[PDB]
Image (tube, rainbow, N blue to C red):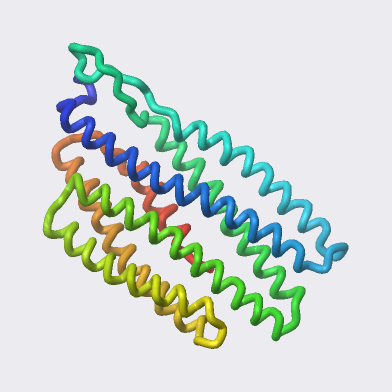
Amino acid sequence: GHMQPNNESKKKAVKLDLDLMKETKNVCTTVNTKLVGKAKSKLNKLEGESHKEYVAEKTKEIDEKNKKFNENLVKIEKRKKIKVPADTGAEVDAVDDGVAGALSDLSSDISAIKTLTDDVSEKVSENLKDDEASATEHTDIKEKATLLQESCNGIGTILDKLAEYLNNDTTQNIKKEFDERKKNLTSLKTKVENKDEDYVTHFRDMATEAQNAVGEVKKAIDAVVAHRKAENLDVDDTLFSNLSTLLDTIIETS
């Protein structure tokens, strides 16, 4: 072994990195498609001629990032097939070292797509009247609530798979908390959809709930990062950094 402490630990570690990346990219692909849709749909709220430059440039960035994100899928789906165990030569798919940079791609494209769509949402607000702009906030609040729900569903699934590797009291507390909080935020997300309820305040509470739950998951991630580092197992802090920060970026709801 050069970077192989033990193959048993390898497959477990790889399973984590695979499930974590998998659920994250599943969320990202969903987020991208939903936000690209939202962005283009809200580009239809602008006057038109007045913002034709804006619509063009932003559509350009969308298409550029779509081709980039769509090739990145084919990139993050890559595995290196290695021989495990080394004796028999059994074919195992390992995520690969380059995937850290691949997450750096993803995180860049996804953070941009969000901020791009956020820009669109702002520009709608300035094209619209105070009343209509407030309805635009209502519109943001709904989609950002949805974005938060989307991310939290994925986050919970990641947490589940993560909690398998380091099934301990700590991950259980986090998972209990996350489950409670998940029921809470799912209820609040439903309240946020009704303008007759104070969707703004419900969003704020829901967001705070999410931050609590997410904070605990983030803490669980760190604990598992530390756990593998503690035994000199395959962990790249930078990989988890891109992951956790993109996690923060998707859950960050403008």
Count of marks overlaid on the render: 0
Name above or below for residue 7 compared with residue 229. above
Name above or below for residue 43 compared with residue 186. above
Q: Quadrant of the N terminus?
A: top left
Name above or below for residue 215 compared with residue 19. below
Q: Residue at x 35, y 21 (%)?
A: 81
In terms of depth relative to the viewer, which is nearer, 213 or 189? Answer: 189
The percent position of residue 103, horizontal first and vertical second, equals: 44, 41
The percent position of residue 17, horizontal first and vertical second, equals: 31, 39
Q: Residue at x 39, y 47 (%)?
A: 23
Q: Quick check: 66 left or right of 241? A: right
Name above or below for residue 201 compared with residue 214. below
Residue placed farthest to the left in the image?
A: 169
Q: Residue at x 70, y 64 (%)?
A: 42
The percent position of residue 194, horizontal first and vertical second, equals: 53, 81
The percent position of residue 165, horizontal first and vertical second, equals: 19, 45
Q: Quick check: 132 left or right of 89? A: right
Q: Quadrant of the C terminus?
A: bottom right
In terms of depth relative to the viewer, which is nearer, 147 or 251? Answer: 147
Q: Residue at x 22, y 48 (%)?
A: 224
Which of the 4 image quarters holds residue 47?
A: bottom right
